[PDB]
Image 1: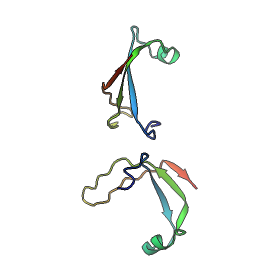
Image 2 (image 1 turned 90 degrees about the vertical axis):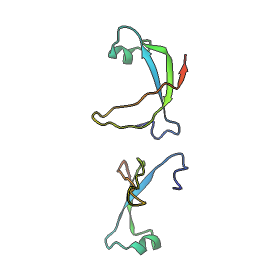
Image 3 (image 1 turned 180 degrees about the horizontal axis):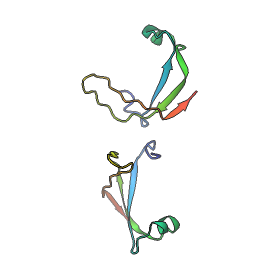
Image 4 (image 1 turned 90 degrees about the horizontal axis):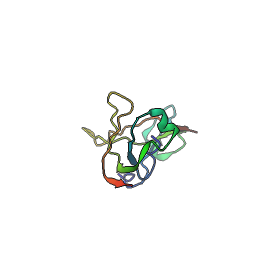
Length: 62
Length: 62
């Protein structure tokens, strides 16, 4: 909801390392892999769940 | 796709002259009439084809 006001809507998707840990995601930023992919949000649906975001791989980066 | 990242997405609508010819459009810019109609894009669908783009008449210009 905070990025809606932004002129450019975009989202980055990364890859987590082995031994996934939800706590470590918020505790340590080194768990996530350096490589990532930035893209543009298409449209929010939130049909049944409040978060149903759509993610696509558009611009890969390291 | 290039205009999606643009802050202001707009599409221009013009009118072709007599003796329609696709090659002349890319070869000579005189074929298309000077008068145009700029308008904003609504939403891309591409249901059957990969290019199905909507045009509206909002701001006429000469």
